[PDB]
Amino acid sequence: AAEGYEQIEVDVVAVWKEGYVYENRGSTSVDQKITITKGMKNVNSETRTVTATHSIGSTISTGDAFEIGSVEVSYSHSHEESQVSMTETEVYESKVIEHTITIPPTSKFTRWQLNADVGGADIEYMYLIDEVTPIGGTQSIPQVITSRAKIIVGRQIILGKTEIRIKHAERKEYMTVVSRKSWPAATLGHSKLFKFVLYEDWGGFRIKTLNTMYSGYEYAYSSDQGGIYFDQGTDNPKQRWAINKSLPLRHGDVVTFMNKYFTRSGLCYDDGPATNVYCLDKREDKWILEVVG
Ligand SMILES: CCCCCCCCCCCCCCCCCC(=O)N[C@@H](COP(=O)(O)OCC[N+](C)(C)C)[C@H](C)O
């Protein structure tokens, strides 16, 4: 939808449910109260980005960040095929609806409830249909023909090609390359000139800097003392990292880089003497990946 994002339509799991049913076996109308809440359960409000609980085809894997642009369902009721679309402002809103009803004599009122599981997100009462039929008379069961959703996610980071920036989530600072002990060393900064390229091989992920002052020494790695420097490409697991998120990596992803040799140590911030980007034991700081325009 926005600069650096892509909208993808995808098939979603939608289901009807008898939301409310009142069987008026007696003569004259009887009144009861009923209230519903149309919208997504446990909406963050501070953000519309939803992390996945379960998959959505091949596009969305678990733990992936997406945004629901819309949800579209096609339903067949009483031999009458129609369809309803739910805009983005409707899914992330908690719309509360309340009202009493007077059911006709010797009749069964039915309010069918439609819900959606768009990658974990439980959109309750997407739609409803108030069907009323006499007691005994076979009512129509609404079926789902095609349930789909339009989701926004972030441009795909093509490994070994797309140039990105690796920002600290908490400090909102970019990871830069400075000199430390005559070697390229990682440290936080505000400069948006420090770009990187992510690779992946048998040994894990690699972080190739494009801004090394010592040419050739360009792959981020953890030393034995814990600090982060850049070295020439080798099969050394100290320059290999493990990302918590599943592939593919997209723009705006929030990830944690865990070293492959120092399996319990992860890429983090630590007020050091010369630099502040380290790879320390029992530490798993979050970093934001973002594509350059
Ligand atoms: C003239 C003489 C008159 C006397 C003659 C005798 C006739 C009497 C018989 C009348 C009985 C009618 C049947 C009773 C109505 C049942 C109501 C019902 O089934 N519906 C439920 C539907 O669940 P929810 O809407 O809560 O979904 C909640 C969904 N969540 C998971 C999001 C929370 C609700 C609670 O109400």
Image: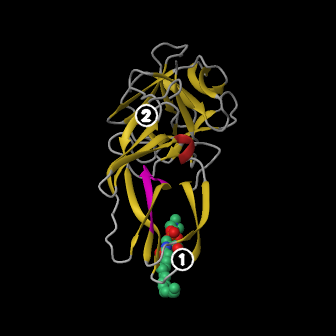
- Camera-side residue: 41 or 214? 41
- Determine the secondary structure under disc 1: loop
> Residue under circle 2?
249
The residue beneath circle 1 is 29
* SS class, disc 2: loop
How far apart marks 2 and 1 lie (CA) works out to 59 Å
Q: Amino acid at mark 1?
A: Ser
Which residue is depicted at the point 48% across and 84% down? 26
Q: Where is residue 227 drawn, in percent x and y?
A: 58, 33
- Depth check: give the residue in front, 56 or 141: 141
In magenta segment, residue 195: no
Q: Is residue 41 visible?
A: no
For the point 55% across and 31% down, the residue is: 228
Q: Is residue 178 left or right of residue 289?
A: right
Observer able to see residue 128: yes
- Residues in magenta? 110-122
